[PDB]
Length: 244
Image (cartoon, rainbow, N blue to C red; front, side):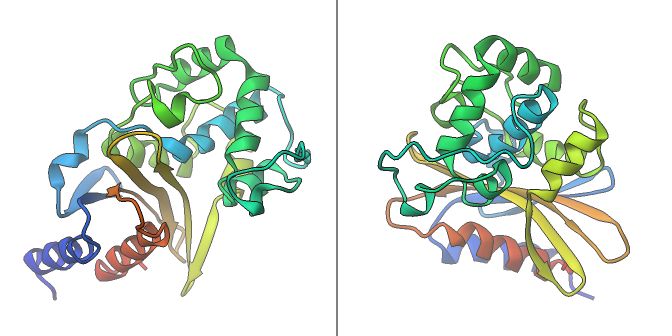
């Protein structure tokens, strides 16, 4: 079998090849393993950016601000991406990472309730500030890569403080890949309105035997880098380690 030294070298190279700095944290049962080319990122705070959609969806569904089939209508105004100029359910919006639909959901929850639920769940630094519709994009909400893989571990195992049914509905929103009997559930995140920019892919692998292996990738995104590098490094890392 392959040495630690070699796994670590391989996964560090994935980051080096992308000309970025990043970490990926894997959790197995209770044990966290940190890999990549900038390990000290593991316990630094960054904005969650679209990572926070997993929790905004939980809070909105639990608090009856939406249902899993409600169609959020496009209001007709020009959007950053053409693929967002359409009507969609929270699940469609999770996959397209459609920030406008999730800003509407935040605004239905409202500042006061949003701040209470973010506190109740203990996400990151728990601080949402005064602006209900952009706190996960530009601050002040922040979360370390450790707290993210721990958040994915809780979601994955249904340990967040929400109805089981709420958690199952949100996890169904997150299936992003199947590869050999393994299912990968994750949400990406790119905070562009912060400097330096932060990229995330947080989730877990469900192996064919039902075991769940949570992960959070966290890297510096750079002007002109592609978004699928978060995916590419993540899948290379998980396959290097035999998780998929």
